Image: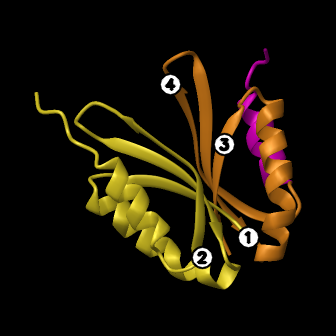
Chain colours: A yellow, B orange
Amino acid sequence: TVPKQIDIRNLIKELRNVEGVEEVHELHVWQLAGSRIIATAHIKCEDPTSYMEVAKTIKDVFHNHGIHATTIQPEF
Amino acid sequence: PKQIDIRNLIKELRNVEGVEEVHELHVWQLAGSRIIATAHIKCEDPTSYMEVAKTIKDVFHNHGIHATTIQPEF
């Protein structure tokens, strides 16, 4: 009975501020029953050493904005 | 306008060069008759992946799925 609010602006800004993230090329969100929100992102990263290190940070940022299921596609 | 042949899709993905493992192969039906897919993929190394990501995208396209997000494990 209670819609969940997604802060687009701070989500995208926090993602862009993750070390080694050069661009967010794609980001979609969609929502299911039980206010469960799913997201995809395509990101440009500096190099594959960054990405493996920083994927956890991205997942944490999503989680901090009430999105618990993500698929992150990097471009190097 | 194409069926998604599930068995061939999984089998083709698994046989893409440098793909070691395919997990979490999800197909989502969204509004406006949109189908997208997500997948977790274990690759040999990041040189393979950047080579293969086009191939995976095209395999998905071939099985009637036009938007994909592939999450690699190195």
Q: Are marks 1 and 2 in contact (CB under 8 Å)?
A: yes
Looking at the picture, does residue B63 appear above or below residue B39?
A: above
Residue nearer the viewer, A7 or B30:
A7
Count residues near mark 4 (Cα–Cα under 10 Å), then give few for <14, some for 14-19, many for 20+.
few
How far apart in space, not on screen, are marks 1 and 3 (Cα)? 17 Å
Q: CA distance from mark 1 to mark 4?
A: 29 Å
Evaluate whether label 1 is on the same chain as label 3.
no
Name the element at disc 3.
strand
Q: CA distance from mark 4 to mark 2?
A: 29 Å
- In the rendered structure, does residue B14 fall within the stretch colored magenta? yes
Q: Which mark is residue A51?
A: 2
Amino acid type, callout 3 = Thr
The amino acid beneath tag 2 is Tyr
Prevailing SS of the magenta stretch? helix
Q: Looking at the rendered structure, which numbered label has been put on residue A42?
A: none
* Distance from Cα at disc 3 to Cα at disc 4: 13 Å
The secondary element bearing badge 2 is classed as helix
Where residue B3 appears, as percent x and y from the top left, is: 75, 19
Q: Residue at x 67, y 77 (%)?
A: A46
Give the structural element (helix, strand or loop) at label 4: strand
Q: Which residues are magenta?
A: B1-15
Same chain for labels 3 and 2? Say yes or no. no
Which residue corresponds to mark 4?
Answer: B30
Q: Is residue B25 visible?
A: yes
Assign the N terminus of chain B to one quadrant of the image.
top right
Label 1 CA crowd tier, 10 Å (few <14, some 14–19, many 20+):
some
Instruction: Provide the residue designation for mark 1.
Output: A76
